[PDB]
Amino acid sequence: RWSITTIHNLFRKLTHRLFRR
Image (cartoon, rainbow, N blue to C red; front, side, top):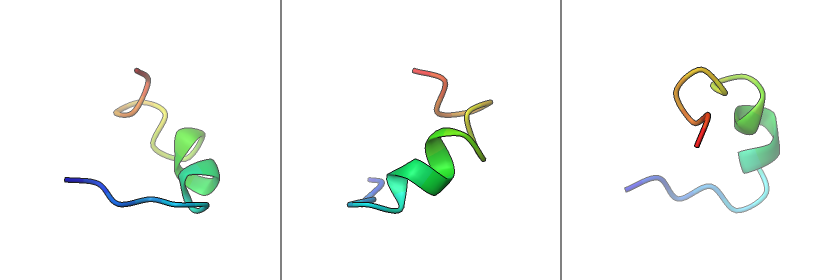
């Protein structure tokens, strides 16, 4: 369970390798 409200932006690119979906 990944609860990322706005931070999702700093992850969508940072962890894009994992959250590529």
